[PDB]
Length: 369
Ligand SMILES: Nc1ccc(-c2ccc(F)cc2)cc1NC(=O)[C@@H]1C[C@H]2CC[C@@H](C1)O2
Ligand SMILES: [Ca+2]
Ligand SMILES: [Ca+2]
Ligand SMILES: [Zn+2]
Image 1 (cartoon, rainbow, N blue to C red):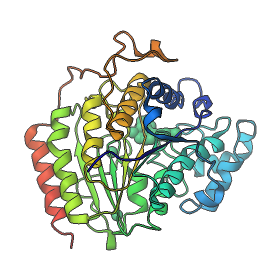
Image 2 (image 1 turned 135 degrees about the vertical axis):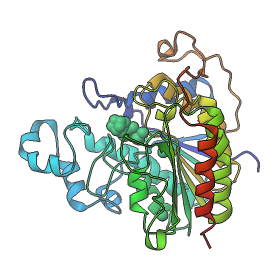
Image 3 (image 1 turned 45 degrees about the vertical axis):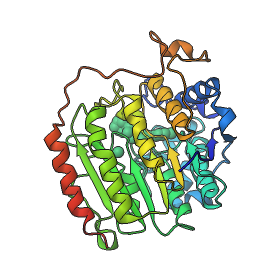
Image 4 (image 1 turned 120 degrees about the vertical axis):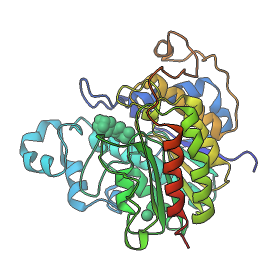
């Protein structure tokens, strides 16, 4: 048990990257998160590092040479010359070309891989990179605002020193890029909780359980609109406890996508910051090397709240509900509190549904050796 060493990765340039007018991804939210947690005094309890810019050598440990070469070359001024490749690599529309795109990929990736190295060297208990968690990016394809899969790269780093790595994903969307990368291996177990049914990315059915050596090492909990703290807490600790018992990982990667929070611009879940952060508390009790990553989140005031509170949880530091003054204080009106209320939206996940899906996942976890 006990309190644990936390290393936290942040680059002050991250907030200046801009996806374009009306695009819901705001890298500014990482700066808001940073500034809020600094104003709570949480810098006093952890080591703050600036990530290196991850190289093409680092990125091509997973991604194709042609895809990384394209990301290094593509700019707003030369887009007409790469019309074929833009379509091939799924760049230009939802994943736009913007100024400094490659540098943005290098920063988000750098934090996750640096955190993994720190964990491998046994120089920290927890590593935190809120700029990471880009779980949709594929080997040779951008997807869902993600270009470079920092998570896959960080897990490959952990696999140098860890026989078994557990990946847990509480983003509202299915962690499809991470699942796909490790679908045929027992050395990574991927566990995703997500909205499923007529929803992006369209994968992560209950019946998707892995293949070959990876059969029974992919776990998917499909959910409906409006899941709440009670319903999520119903199943999270039981599932993760059973996974820990059967799989026995030596390192953990937790993707903490904040688009599962109540009031998210794109999401349809109803979790509070406390309900979301209960997942961090559950994972942290197992006392394994832990990489905590960001993810989605489009109501940026709540993203800042969520990841500030989850940093406090990682540190075992109680922080007051009254928000301290900060550079983005006006974003947190009209209440200026840390914690959020759930909406009155209907929870389409019945208690019977939650128990039934849990029981079917328990059947699959019995098939581990
Ligand atoms: N899930 C996720 C996780 C991380 C990042 C992400 C991407 C780049 C970053 F620098 C940091 C985080 C994005 C998503 N993308 C979504 O949530 C969108 C997927 C599609 C398109 C609109 C809607 C929402 O459906
Ligand atoms: Ca998920
Ligand atoms: Ca697997
Ligand atoms: Zn998401």
